[PDB]
Amino acid sequence: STIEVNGQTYLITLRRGDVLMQGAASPELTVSGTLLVEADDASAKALATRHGLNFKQSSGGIALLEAKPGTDLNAIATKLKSEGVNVQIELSGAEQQPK
Amino acid sequence: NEGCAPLTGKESGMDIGRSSTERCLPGANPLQDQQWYLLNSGQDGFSARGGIAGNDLNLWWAHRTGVLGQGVNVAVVDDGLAIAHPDLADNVRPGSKNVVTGSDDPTPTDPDTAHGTSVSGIIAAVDNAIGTKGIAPRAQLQGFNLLDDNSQQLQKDWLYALGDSNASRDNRVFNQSYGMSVVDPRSANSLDQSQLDRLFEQQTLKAQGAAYIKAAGNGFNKIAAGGYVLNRTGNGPKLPFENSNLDPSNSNFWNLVVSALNADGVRSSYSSVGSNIFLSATGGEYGTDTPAMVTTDLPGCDMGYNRTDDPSTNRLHGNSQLDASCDYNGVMNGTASATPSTSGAMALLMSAYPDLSVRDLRDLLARSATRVDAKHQPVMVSYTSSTGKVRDVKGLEGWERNAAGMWFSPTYGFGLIDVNKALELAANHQPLPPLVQLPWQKINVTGSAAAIADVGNSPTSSTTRIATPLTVEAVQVMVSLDHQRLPDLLIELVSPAGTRSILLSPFNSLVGQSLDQQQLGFVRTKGLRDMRMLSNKFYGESAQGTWRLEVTDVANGTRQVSLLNRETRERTTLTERNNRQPGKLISWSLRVLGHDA
Ligand SMILES: [Ca+2]
Ligand SMILES: [Ca+2]
Ligand SMILES: [Ca+2]
C-alpha cells in the first residue's frame, strides 16, 4: 500500500522498525523511532513529556525525540503539525554511499 | 627519496612548478615513488601503464620545506578505519567511534570494507620506512564508521561524526568520501539536512574553522541506488548522468565539492561534474590498466582490497616481495580519493598558515589551481523546435573565464590543486572580510511567461535584482517547476556581468518519473520542489544588478536507460517518454554568499 510520510509517498500507523520502500531504485528505509522537531530545548522538552516521547539531544535548534515501544509515530507527527510544529520522522538506511 | 634534501624555503629563484629541476620528495617509504598523486613522474602505480608527468597535487615544495600537516585534526567519516594499521596508528588521535558497536575502535569486520582505511592513508599515512607517505603525514586522524554495512546512518551518528560531539568538534577537516545518487529530485529543506547545514556553518565560521570536503560522485556514466545500477544506452551527448548538483548536500556551500582527475591529467572517466565543483583532485582510474591510488589497505592478506580471495591485476596485490602482509593496495580510486587528496592539501595549508580561515584557504586554492585540460570542448545538445528551428545549445561548458578574471569549468572547478602555488600565495595573503549571506529572494512566476514548451525556441526566463553591493563567492538557487520528463531540462543562471553557469545539465539521472510509471503505474514526481543548486562560476564578481534563471526543454526524442538488478543480474530497459504537455516554472529563489570588499 501507499503511505504518506514527511510529505512524500512510500510503499509499505507507523511504528519503530517498520520498513518502507520508496519505489524501486532507492534503499530500503526503516522507521528508526526518532523524531526531529524544530523547537528550542525547553519547548522540545515540554513537547516530549506531553506527547509521551523522550528528549534525547539537540543541535541547531532541532531536537531528537525518541518514541517508546508501541508508539504510532505518524499519529504523533500529524498532531505536532496541527500544533504548528515542524517535525520529521527519521527514516534510516543506506542513503549515503562510498564514492 | 633519502637523496631529496630539505629546502630552506627561501632559495632565490626557486621554480615551484610541476616540471621544476628541484621537484622531488623526501622520505624512505618504500611505496612513495608509486604514489603518482604526490609526484607524477609518469609512473604506473603498479598498473599496466603510467600517465603524464606533472599531473599531481604539486606538493613537493611543501614536503621539502617541512609543511606536513602538523597540528591539523582530520575526521574520516566513512566505512571504518583500521586504527592499528602500522602505517596509520602513530597518526590516530583519541575520539574515533564505532557507531555499530559503540566502541572507540572503528576497525571493520568485513574484508571488503577497506574504503575508509584507504581514504585515511591518502591523507596521513605515516612518514617512516614502511608503506606509503601521506599527503599530510603529520596530520592526526579520527574515524567514524557511518558507512559500515550495519550502520543505519542515524542522525545522532552523523552529528557525532561531523562536529557536534566533544570528540569531533575540534577537527579542522571533515573528510566525506561519500554521496547520494538520486533518480528523483529532493528538497534540501528537510530537518535532517537543515540540522547538518547549521552544524557545518557553525563549524566552518568559528575560530580555527573546519573545512568540510565532499566527493562529487562517480556518476558520469552510471549510478547505483538500492541494489540497481542505471546507465544510459544509445548515442546521446557526452553529458554527465550524475550532475553533482543532484545530491542536495553538494549545494550547501559548507561542503567543498571535488571532482576526480586521472594520471593523464584529465577528468577520471567516472567523475561527476557540475557548477558546484570547487576543485579537481587526484583520484585515478582503477589501478589495473592505468594508475589509481596506492595507499593503506586493511591489514593482512585476509582483509581489504589487497587480499588473497580478491585478486587484482595491480602488481602490488598478493605480492610477497613488495607487500608481504598485504597492508597496502593500488586500486583505491573515485571522487572518494579526490576528497582525501583535498583534505590532505587543506591540512598542509592549515599547518603552514594556522590563522587562515576556511574561506581564506578556499580563496588560495582557487587562485592557485592549475587549468588542466585547457582545450576540452563544451558539450552541445541538438534538437529541432516546434517551429522547425534547428538549435545547438551548450549542455556543459568547457573552461570559461568570469568577469573577475577567474577561470572555471564544471569538470575541474577552478582547476587541479597546486599546493606549492597555494603556499606561495599564502605567504602574502590578506584575510577576506566576514561572510555575508544575503537573504533569499523568492520569485513566484505567473501567467504565460511560466510556460516551458517542449523543445523550446528559447529559454523560459525569470529575473531578479540584487541591490546590495557584494563580491560573490557562491550562489545558491532553489527551483520549483512542473515537467513530465525532468532530464529534458537545461537550467542556467546569468549574472549582472552576463556570465553564464549551467546549474543543471540535461539528460541527467532524474529518470524516476519513467521508473515510477514502469514499476508502479503512476508518477510521484510532478517536477522540482525547492531543488537546490550551487554555482562557483561567479567567484569574485559584483553581485549588484539583475540575475536571470533560464530553463529550456531541449529534447523530444525517446531515450532508453539500462537497469541492472545487482542481485538477480536481470537487465531491464526503461524508456523515457517525451512530455505530452508543456512544463511550468513555478518559482525560484536566489541566495548570494560573499563579502563586502
Ligand atoms: Ca609510511
Ligand atoms: Ca589487506
Ligand atoms: Ca521534451
Image (tube, coloured by chain):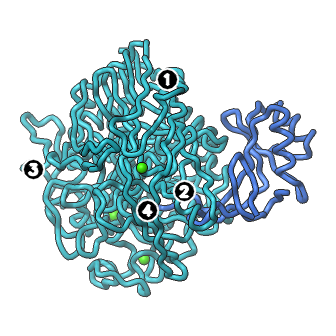
Mark 2, chain letter? Answer: B
Foreground disc of the pair 3, 4: 3
Image-quadrant location for residue B547: top left
| Element class at badge 2 | helix
Image location of residue B493, percent across then percent down: 37, 32
Residue B502 position, x and y percent, is 34, 39
Q: Nearer the viewer, residue B151 or A81?
A: A81
Residue indicated by mark 4: B88
Q: Residues within 10 Å of mark 2 (few under 14, many from 20)?
A: many
Q: Which chain is blue?
A: A
Residue found 38% across the figure and 36% down from its top: B535
Tag 1's secondary structure? strand
Question: How far apart in space, not on screen, are marks 3 and 1 (Cα)?
Answer: 41 Å
Circles 3 and 4 on the same subunit: yes
Residue corresponding to mark 1: B437
**Could you tell me which residue is drawn at 72 percent across and 39 percent down?**
A58
Left or right placement of residue B532 versus residue A69 in this view: left
Compare residues B401 and B554 and report the one nearer the observer.
B554
The residue that disc 3 covers is B19
- Circle 3 Cα neighbour tier, 10 Å, few/some/many (<14 / 14–19 / ≥20): few
Assign a secondary structure to mark 4: loop
* Residue named by callout 2: B513
Q: Is residue B437 left or right of residue A3?
A: left
